[PDB]
Length: 255
Ligand SMILES: [Cl-]
Ligand SMILES: [Zn+2]
Image (cartoon, rainbow, N blue to C red; front, side, top):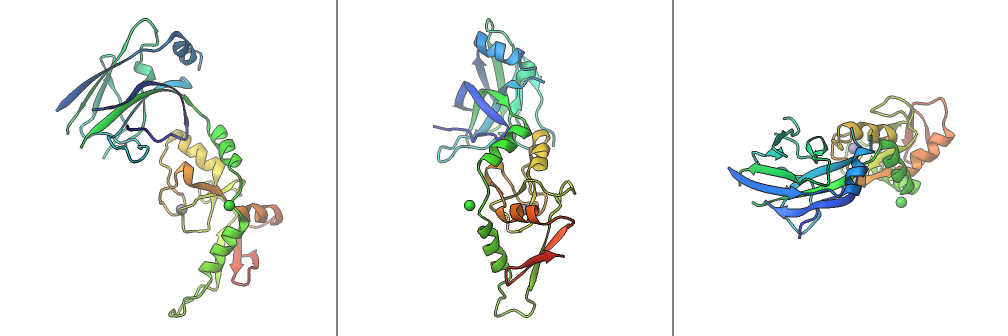
């Protein structure tokens, strides 16, 4: 079977349409229970939503959102708006077009051109950046020795090299927000030592979810994020300072 990869800002409450294989046309139907209708209507933009998701019809791993080509969706006979322009594949909030009643069915008509694709619908709670931050801080702090070993590595001179890096420089300020770091974080896959502010980075992806490193522009998914232990200890010792300089001998001082 096909499963979707969980979204960091969405907690699945129920599955309304299980992942189902898709100028082609396919018709879908689903119903909400009175309890599910009550959850939506009392969630104030609603915080409990109906989420439509598309992906590749692949089984080896949980799938990320992937729109089929020439996608055009109709929810309850009404044209469903998609992300602007190539078009980025993302979950679709169909709550504004949903029939928020237990007494009537909801209809989805999908048009695309032919690889196989899959469609699924979920009842979700949209989480805040604050909640996602607390979930991140709950995974703990990365060993400060992991950064110390990375610093040592980068300052280890290549023997068949003329120009050798004798010292590294990092900032204690966020490269995105310009204020001093509170939660210094980075993706595990990033090669650089420069961290960015975790709270600010989640505040940004709450609105527009690009999950892109503000330092190197590589992918920085939520599930790859760590809190640098070394920068956590420095942020506690250091005071009137912007940039730190690291030596080979392990020492550090202002830059
Ligand atoms: Cl660790
Ligand atoms: Zn990066």
